[PDB]
Image (cartoon, rainbow, N blue to C red):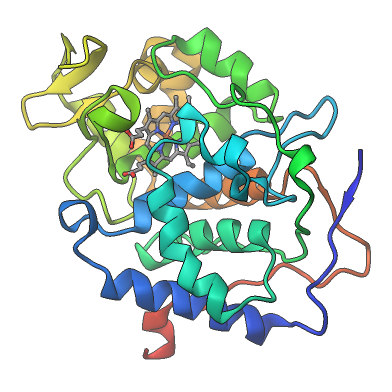
Length: 291
Ligand code: HEM
């Protein structure tokens, strides 16, 4: 099963920087969402969920086909809450109807990371919408109540190794769990709409207690009001993951560079780029443009 990137007809870097900027300006404007967290975190989770359905064995799933727009995937229990991200991006799609759905959802996550002061994430265009019957079945996104061996095995299906898994999980410094969406409640730190390495610092430095929440699920909670999923906490229970947690807690730049590479890879899994494809784009932030 081969998915070849096909650039939206006649488009180039400037076109996609315009779409970036529209997303970024709306991120700035719609600041009230989720008790003033803003839409940045949910856009990052949307880009990950539309990509995290990929299966390396048969190239099903993945960001290419934009299939989150179809009911079966939109209504996956694992995707509860991401409707808010889709609705955010709808007026953007209306203004730029030429962009593919996969390109929009993945660009929304790149834009959110960068606007939240995260690393630059190179991004490539050319995902092509595919029909409803190419939508992957529910059940391909991971469970949160599991341990390190589950996490490790899960991510082999996405061709991610230990370092890439630990780097990607640093996105859990962003946003929060919502009890009605996932049966978990609370944020993982204090700066949860700024992209930093706080997730690793908090795993190492907080005093975590294993508690039950109001949905009767266990999670790790700290007296500062932070929380970790069981799969988050597994990163300090496993000695291989713990080493990498310590590395990223002690080196902000290294985390940013490893995250950028793993996140681009996540967003590009499944896609074949022609040798003649444009090189990846690195968008300027609004701040860098004086906008
Ligand atoms: C073992 C792997 C993972 C599990 C089990 C997991 C699970 C969760 C759960 C249960 C939530 C809460 C959803 C809610 O209640 O609204 C969450 C939120 C989130 N996840 Fe993950 N996740 C994983 C990996 C990742 C990855 C790889 C990324 C991106 C790189 C990511 C980004 C996020 C973001 C940014 C949020 C906050 C969303 C919000 O505030 O609306 N997750 N995740």
